[PDB]
Every structure is written in C-alpha cells, then in structure tokens.
Length: 131
Length: 131
Image (cartoon, rainbow over the protein chains, first blue to last red):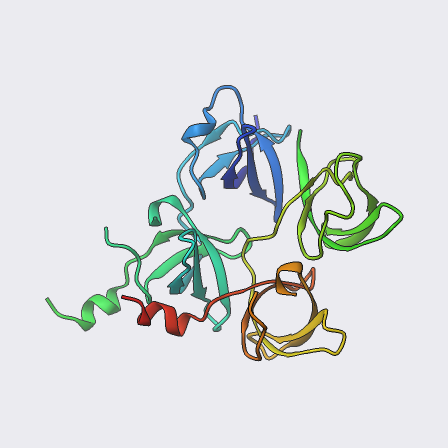
C-alpha cells in the first residue's frame, strides 16, 4: 500500500524513464497499466517498493522560486538566478514550453531535482505598470 | 531493471575506471560490451546493483554556474569561483580541451564531482542582442 513519489526527467526508446527520488536519479520501467508515451518531463510519478512507476499525477506546486535570466538556445534549459545570486541552469517542464517566458519571470523550481515547473505571477510587476 | 548513474573520473589500463556516485568514489570494472578506450573524462556512466559500468553517455543537467579565473600549468584542471567567493580547482571534461577558454567564462560544474562540463553563454548578451 505505501507508495513514494519522484520527479520524471526524460523518456527512452526502451520504454524506460529517469526518476529523481531521495536525492538520486534512477532508471525505472513504467508499469503495464500506464502508457509511456503520455508521460511528460517534470511530471510527478508514483513509485513503489519495487521501484516501478505506477501512476503519474500533476506537477509540484511548492518549492523555491527563482528569477529567470535567459533561455538557452537548445530550448530545453533555462539559466536562472537563486535568492542569494546563485545561478543555476535548470530544465524546463512541459507547461513552460500564454506568451513565451521573458527574462525577469519567476519560476517555481527545486534545485535538487533541477526543474522549473510553473511560472508564478508577481503582484509587484503588475502594480508597477498600471492598467 | 533498476539502475543508478555515476560520473567517470579516470581510466586505467587494468580495465578498471573510477566512478563517483552516492557521494563517494569507487574503482569498478567495466562490462565486456563497453570499450574502456572509448570512455572520456567528465562523462556520465550507468551502473547497476552489482556496480557494473554498462552504458556510457554525457552529462547535461543542472549545476552552479562557476566563474573561471585561470587555467593551471598542466592544462587539465581549472580554477573556478562560485556565488559565495569560494575558489576551487576542478578537472576539465573532454569537450573543454571548441573555442579557447578565457578568464571569466561561465562554466557548468558539479562540486561533489569536481568537473566542469560545458560553458554557458553569457545571459547579459543573448537575451538582448538577438532580434
């Protein structure tokens, strides 16, 4: 009955996936119940004691928030700046790739996993330019 | 089958290579399928529960952006500083030994592994100059 959680990283042609869990990256096989094609990068995946992906839910809603600096030319990574001016090159999740992200946008990230899940609207920038 | 990952440090003629994983370095033998000479410095390897190097690859993930200060005499190690003015020497990877390196170039590094993997293009330029 007890089942853990992990962060999906990428998909492989061997019907295998990379899962970040307990601060470590592991190679896992999707269960026959789920379809490996429907999986998306950065999506939370439910694991088990046998280390098998059995269900994928939505994306994480809590964690750190960082300021976006730039989007790399490859289109799958973004350079952002942490709270103490620490700079990280983090993967972009599927929802991030409205308008395309611009420098200065705030992204919800978890540094250990290294993914940007959601653009978080800021009230200060909205208040600066009155409408 | 579940499996983990590690970072390759060096290769020896004894068909044994040094791999950093789980926060520690171990000298392990490679599988017969893979070729020892084919492996390069600074690239990832895939381990197993028996710790057998079965698959190769390259490292492309997050990392604290480090400012390169200078290149040492031997030409295989580089001095980099971090956000907290922490100076440390790191082994250069194969793809960095490309344009000639210069002081102040941003680099992608793994502090636990001590390897610089790639040079991140400057954010202050690309996000603005392009049109």
